[PDB]
Image 1 (cartoon, rainbow, N blue to C red):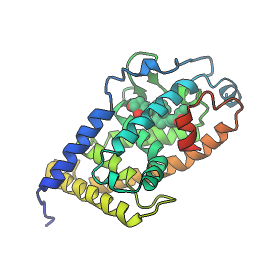
Image 2 (cartoon, helix red, strand yellow; image 1 turned 180 degrees about the horizontal axis):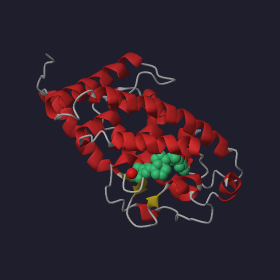
Image 3 (cartoon, protein in one colour; image 1 turned 90 degrees about the vertical axis):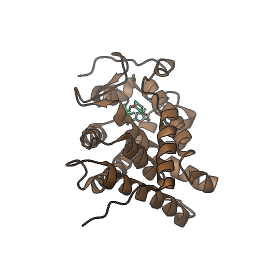
Amino acid sequence: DSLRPKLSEEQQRIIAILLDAHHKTYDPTYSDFCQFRPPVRVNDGSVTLELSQLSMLPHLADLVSYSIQKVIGFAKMIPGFRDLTSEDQIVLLKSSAIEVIMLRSNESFTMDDMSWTCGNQDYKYRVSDVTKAGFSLELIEPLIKFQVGLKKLNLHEEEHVLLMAICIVSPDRPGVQDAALIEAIQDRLSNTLQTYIRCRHPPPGSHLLYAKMIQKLADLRSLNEEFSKQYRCLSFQPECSMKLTPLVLEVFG
Ligand SMILES: C=C1C[C@H](C[C@H](C)[C@H]2CC[C@H]3/C(=C/C=C4/C[C@@H](O)C[C@H](O)C4=C)CCC[C@]23C)OC1=O
């Protein structure tokens, strides 16, 4: 009964632009990673030790900062994003940043050992590394769970880049001015996604896929809520700002 309309020339363009944007802003070789402050790993197995040393914070804070820059570059290439006021663009970028980082990080996440494998042994990021950066299991365990859930969706890159675009351009973000314009841009991206799934995705991965993707966006809201708490707690640690970056401090502060 459900119709399967073809992708319009505009919808085909949007996909092309977004695939192009991601390829311009996501390096699948992770070759810039050696330019960050070195990853330091010590003995642990302790929250007191974690906050005392914060050995993995300078490296992962440089990684996140770097990733924010890429997300910013990616957002500016979303069809319609430049039409928004620069004030609204920043509100959207600032509230979605960590969520899009979690989304895009899926490309490096592997279910072989439940880590983010960005090559090497140094640039393999386990759960233990994230605690060494001063974050608790309240964030990390649901994050890993989200990563696995998203991986099992076996998303086409097209679906993957549209989901990030939809995540960024969200009318229901605190502090937004022209919510009508943001919703209009999101709807254009959402229809493209819904149309893509219905006429490009083969069974049984096609059935109810869009609803599962919308649910992942809701999971991202929860992780962002928890991340915000933990970042606030982390910022209370003396001499913490040096371990972070001016960009990380503004976006999350
Ligand atoms: C210093 C930190 C760490 C924390 C980041 C959180 C806890 C998670 C979210 C995604 C995770 C990771 C993502 C991995 C990558 C590598 C690559 O896929 C690019 C992608 O943008 C990315 C960030 C691995 C370590 C912990 C990260 C950064 O926030 C911070 O500011």
